[PDB]
Structure formats: C-alpha cells, structure tokens
Length: 279
Image (tube, rainbow, N blue to C red):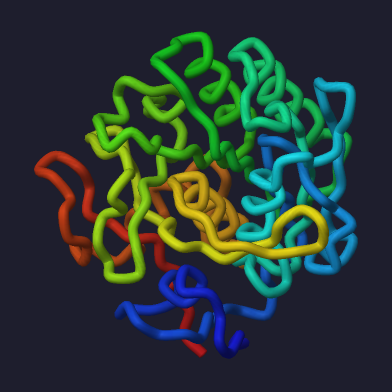
C-alpha cells in the first residue's frame, strides 16, 4: 500500500533515504494488534481514529484530552493519515493532567493497569504500549516499565528532551524497554533529543504533523513524537508475525537503517526505525 504525500516521518520509516513523501506499508496496518497510549488521553471522536480509539482508564476528574499531547501521539500510532499501524486498536490511559504533568505514583499505576487490562481486551496479534513521558531517575518508575515489558507488552518510551544522557531520566533509563531518540527530516539528531547507551533506536521527531484535540491537527517536536512511530511500527511487525512483544525492539534495531544520522555522539546507537517493506 502507499500513502501519497504522507508526513515526513511516516515516509522516513519505510524509506532507505530521507526526503521522500510516500509511506509504504503492508495492508495489514496493525489489524489484530493493540497499542496503549499512556499520556494525557485521547480524542477518540476524531474522524482520524475511525472509532478505533477508546479511553479505558483515567486518574483525573475527566478522561478528556484537554491538552492535545496524548491525541498527537495516538495519531502517529494508528490514525488513518498520520499513523504507522492504521488498523491498530488504540487504548487511552490518561496518566497526565491537562498541563502534561502527572506524579510518578500515578504513572506507575498506569503501567500496572495495562499489563492486566490487556487480558480483558482482544488482541490476537499482541500488545504495544507507548510512553511519551519521563522525568528524573526513578527506580520504582523503571521497575514499573520493566513489569509492563515481561508481562507481554512491547514498551517504547521517549528518551527525553534534555539534550543530555538518558541514563538520568526514567523510564527512559530502563534496559528492558525500548528507548526511542528523536531525529529530523535531514537525518540529523534532533536538537533536543537525549542520547546515551540506553537508547535502542531513533524515530522521526522534529516537525511531526499529527492529530490534535478539537478535531484538528498540528506539527510539534519532541522525543514524544519519536516514541509512537516505533510503537506503531512494533504493532505493525507483530500483526505480520515477524516479531513478538518480547523481541520487537531488538527486531527493530536489527532491521533498522544502520548509521545514517548526523550528530550522534560516541556511545549512542546510530539506528533509525525502518519497516523493510517490499511491495
């Protein structure tokens, strides 16, 4: 299949070279898989979600996305125009408030919810979880992310926007879960992206167009935009049978575009999320 005039990140993930504008992917589009978006929530009403998104949990007076952040991220996982796995089922777990904030104990609660809630939901192709969030080092927070992983969920988390080492941020610094760094349309390392040995893969994350609250769209930047392409991609390769939850991140990094990114410091991996799809 081909999306003509796709966003620069969608094209980059099915492209051996930057600067193209057609995203190339198997019709499967993640049908049969499920991706939990742990964030400020989702705007499931968006035409872009086609009723494939639904809120399943919240910790605040509302489960509405009064921010846009979570809605922006879910649009990169499975929205028809902006997402990677365009038939995936999205589940919203609102752990962040409408300012994009939330305490650690709440985030921990959220991951704990997904590993159990997957058992009530129907996902014969496997489960993914996107965590475009982070903060200072926390081992409690890291164990939470590691618990989500060994339970049968493919975790991708943002490496951080501090332009520093990701070993001092959680859950970014947890070795069992997949830590996505950010790059731009010129295959540069994103200005803001954290780096470090803990990273597993880079995904598109500068000037990322995607769904927004109010039935709209907008372009914003961050490792939070890098996290959902890998998330969607994981769910894409799981539907195909090419990988499983527990080995997708190593699968992605194995089959990724080796060594095409400028400004990667020594010690940080030079791998760019890629879908090796052959029409």
